[PDB]
Picture 1 (tube, rainbow, N blue to C red):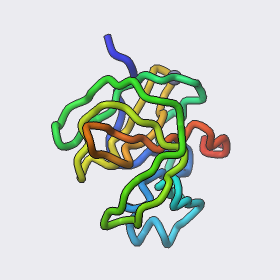
Picture 2: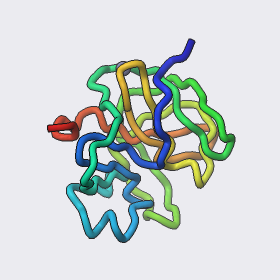
Picture 3: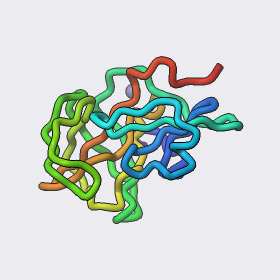
Length: 149
Ligand SMILES: [Zn+2]
């Protein structure tokens, strides 16, 4: 019994002809094939040729399970709704307010960004931030165009 689906953990969400990755980890190839990006959400979407098997959740769940790479293990989480959160400077961004970010208590060290959070409806978001015993997930549920055709 689990608080969310187990699915692929490729470091990116694959749905329809889209690949959703942490903007700060997007590869040179992602940028050559850019569909959409938002620095304030730490999200980038690039285009693909082949159908991805993830389902994007369209719910208001505040519980789910994510994969933590540093522990090589899944954890159930309770997270706050998507909010505007102050994220201090890193090698990837200056200090700024990051929007659509969902906070939970959880392990999240550098390297853990890209871990996928799923509820029982599908993919909810992707690990983006960490620190002070918290893990922050970039929500993708509001992206209605992000789907299959
Ligand atoms: Zn849900």
